Image (tube, rainbow, N blue to C red):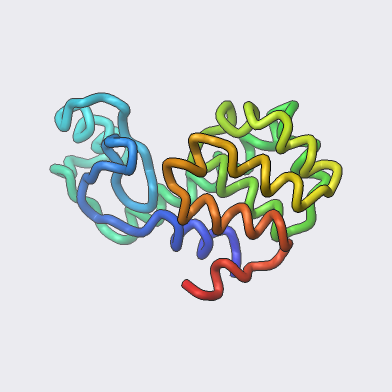
Length: 164
């Protein structure tokens, strides 16, 4: 398993504009288009994103190309972030995938806010950190996905995804 397969499981793949769990306009593999309520604002961001008149529908290839960029941007974001970088550097390869997953979902800013959890991860207190991460809107809102990510941090294995 790898970050790509992992995220592909957590986000799914949709070739037509859809609303995400928060009610926002999304397409492909969890690619947020706009927080705006206008389907029209969404289609416009979409076309700009793809470079063609999509009319709200994209191909598998287009979806994947957006996905590749988003993963790259997630990694680079962590590497540039002063709160995130040190945690990332401290982690083994599987857990690193878990931090990338959070960042792809909630943005750099969002994850950087999990101050206490970040400190625990850095200190390698797995169980403690898993408990702290669960005390969040994040866990409350998307508990199935949050549980898979948390288990990944707790065990350092891909068990939670081997199921799926």
